Image (cartoon, coloured by chain):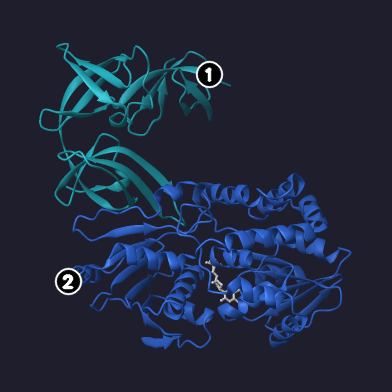
Amino acid sequence: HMKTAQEFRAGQVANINGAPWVIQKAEFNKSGRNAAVVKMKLKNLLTGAGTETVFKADDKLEPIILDRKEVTYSYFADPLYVFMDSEFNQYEIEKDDLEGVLTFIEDGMTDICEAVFYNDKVISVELPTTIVRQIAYTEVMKTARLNNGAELQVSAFCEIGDSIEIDTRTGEYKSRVK
Amino acid sequence: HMASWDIFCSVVDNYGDIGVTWRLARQLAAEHGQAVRLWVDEPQAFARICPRADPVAHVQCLDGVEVRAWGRPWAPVAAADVVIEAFACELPEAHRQAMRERKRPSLWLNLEYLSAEEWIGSCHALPSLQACGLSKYFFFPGFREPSGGLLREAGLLERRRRFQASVSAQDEFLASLGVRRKVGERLISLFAYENPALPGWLEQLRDARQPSLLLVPEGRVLADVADWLRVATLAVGDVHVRDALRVQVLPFMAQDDYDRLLWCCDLNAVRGEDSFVRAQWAGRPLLWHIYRQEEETHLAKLEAFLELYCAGLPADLAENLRTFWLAWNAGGGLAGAWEGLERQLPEWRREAQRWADEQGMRPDLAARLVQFYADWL
Ligand SMILES: Cc1cn([C@H]2C[C@H](O)[C@@H](COP(=O)(O)OP(=O)(O)O)O2)c(=O)[nH]c1=O
């Protein structure tokens, strides 16, 4: 039950020497030749301590699969983000625990997210594997921008105001509506 | 205190893997009194940059360094106080277990590749949390802070200034290589990979107004020079004249003699990472053939150094520099760029000296490794 360090994403948890660490931020960097480096911002899930670690892209870590519960986004308080489940329970999440959602977060977001729990305590929120975003600006593929300002490569057939699908595990274009 | 250091060097290709680790190993023994074991899996490559080395010996002592062949299969031995896997190579599994069976487990360091990109600063000196509890950190060389600095021997720039200010010292060294510069000749060294832009540049040196002496160490670029010279074979000691261009083939020399070669020339064409830095210590204009990577990853690394290196340059000199290096690493098209650089060679030289002297004020990488280990105890 081991995973490659470059396969981890924000919001996931790894078991490192008996300590459960939540990954608040994962960044990929290409070093020399074919080598690569993954920098991680971690937070201990029992003592709360935070640390930064670095791995080879091929290094193997033991993930920890956690409970989940469907949740949706409501508004942005300061400086916390509030999420609500199907039973109108509020979940206030810090900005450091939402680096996976912040890339495609939008006002009035209709996506059905999943809150990651560690012993009945929410630690992060994950977007669905596929999301539907509208293109706010654009000129095989070309550069476009979404309503929240993010930049990603989309199909050249797309235009202003079209609907596209995004794969949140990669943050890349998937398809578009006719 | 005298601590033992294991340095594992995997020669993937070329010579920069063993060049950097040998330079580091030699410096930890000489000016820090450390015990060093240099493990290299391609002893033939080490013998190329160290002529005194025996390429067939399993172990030999050179300049206070214990150089061992990295054999396959690996023979288990005791681990040193510090274990360095250079360039993110993979340690032997049995050696990682020897690192744990000690009163104080070995300090584990990954000496990463050299890059001028900003991301290496946030990763330098960060821990690499191991599932076994071994204390591992990544060590990034760098041109700016924060980083691990650059490899620089004690008194290197002082010896380079005394050498360049002595006409007799420069002529005596060149005479040891069988080289005599003609009056008014411009000296250029050529160390690169297979470069399609080379013949176009040689044509400009051939048709130029000032004569040039191109000193080419034996290597991969010789086939391109021979094709341009239109000769079948180029051997060490050959001298060919093409109008204002003189081409002489030099032998692959010891690492310290390669320094003195770079110190003699007005323009050093270098490559990789070690000779790239060595040309910077020379305080002379530089031409960099960066190691090509997939998906044009090296272009970001080339631009990152250029943006940092061209900070003190005037705008027109910085533009000619970026255009030439880009053409030097991505197909010909450096005609007008070379004409612009050739006109401003004195000014470029003065800025190359300032860049070396400012870099020379930063503590060297070997000293940062010792301070890192001392503060880690
Ligand atoms: C040309 C030459 C290089 N060298 C050394 C300098 C450098 O340490 C090494 C080249 O390493 P480097 O500059 O990193 O480039 P690459 O990895 O592509 O080979 O070879 C010599 O020792 N003698 C020489 O004559």
Residue A38 point in image, percent of width and height: 36, 47
Q: Badge 2 sits on which subunit?
A: B
Q: Which mark is residue B101?
A: 2
In the image, the chain rendered in cyan is A
Question: Ligand 1 closer than 8 Å to the CB at disc 1?
Answer: no
In which chain is the residue bearing label 1? A
Return the residue found at the far left: A119
Position of residue B292 measured from the top left corner of the image (x, y, whole percent): 55, 56
User: In whole angstroms, how far apart are the C-alphas of marks 2 and 1?
Assistant: 60 Å
In the displayed structure, B95 sits above or below B201; it is below
Disc 2 secondary structure class? loop
**Considering depth in this image, is B356 or B237 the residue closer to the camera?**
B356
Vertical placement of residue A106 versus A65, above or below:
above
A56 relative position to B22: left or right: left
Give the secondary structure at mark 1: strand
A54 vs A134: above or below: below
Residue A63: tell me if it is visible: yes
Residue B327 in the image, given as x and y percentages of width and height? 68, 52
Badge 2 and badge 1 in a common chain: no
User: Mark 2 belongs to which amino acid?
Assistant: Glu
Using a 10 Å C-alpha cutoff, classify the residue at mark 1 as few (fewer than 14 neighbours), some (14 to 19) or many (20 or more). Answer: some
Instruction: Report the residue at 48% width, 77% height from top.
Output: B45
Q: Which of B196 and B363 is in front in this view?
A: B363
- Chain ID, blue in image: B
Tell me where residue A25 appears, x and y as whole percent.
33, 38
B193 left or right of A148? right
